[PDB]
Length: 132
Length: 132
Ligand SMILES: OC[C@H]1O[C@@H](O[C@H]2[C@H](O)[C@@H](O)[C@H](O)O[C@@H]2CO)[C@H](O)[C@@H](O)[C@H]1O
Ligand SMILES: OC[C@H]1O[C@@H](O[C@H]2[C@H](O)[C@@H](O)[C@H](O)O[C@@H]2CO)[C@H](O)[C@@H](O)[C@H]1O
Image (cartoon, rainbow over the protein chains, first blue to last red):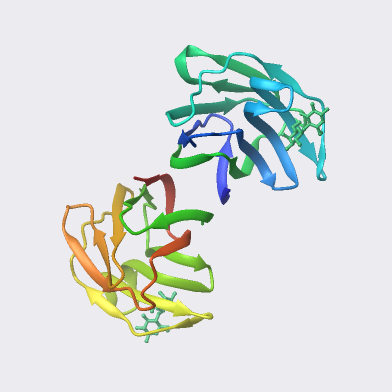
């Protein structure tokens, strides 16, 4: 998927990602961190991934190893349709605004103040990234 | 600055890049191609870079070697202020729409139907990328 590197996404900023879910999507993720092996925030939108049907799975990855999962069954996503998601954070917590007023919080496990890497993976097409 | 890798920019698509020019900018470039070293379209916005004052320099880079330059004196950019440009192409030509709505042309020297890499260099910061 699309990898955005050498950006500065730090305290007090927001990041919005727009995309269109593919027609027969299985899943797509948005990822914020340092690299494909260091991810502070993985938001996996699972349409049908094993036992996870219309479920968001959140995690972090450290040295290419997945940590402890969190799940949400609020799933305002539809195959073939546009979405926007907005992320902000402080040293404690990521705040994720999903479509249709849904919201998920996920811990900022290392208390990082800035990230340099954003990555959209799987069954969605990027339409835009806005960061300020 | 920002590198965007594995972006799918094909014939028929419009790539818009937006951001803010540094307050005492000397130059910044938007680059479309395959990597830092492999650029089909380099658009260098030169406020002040040697003999180029308020000049756009366009070129391509093959295997880390610059090719033949082209210049334009249409320069609707201001240090410290926002900018946005929209890039399109067919198999022959790139079309670059500047902030005042006017277009500059540059040859598609390799006659490619898709590119996969964008990056910004220099005295500006990216705040937005869109594909439509
Ligand atoms: O945690 C995100 C990570 O999940 C992996 O799949 C997990 C699965 O979610 C879980 O239920 C099972 O117990 O373990 C699997 C392997 O850790 C995905 O493979 C990976 O791509 C991420 O999405
Ligand atoms: O061609 C784009 C390339 O230009 C380099 O600068 C050139 C300059 O434009 C030219 O007038 C002079 O003769 O040579 C310089 C060095 O080749 C930039 O340094 C490079 O970053 C690109 O912008």
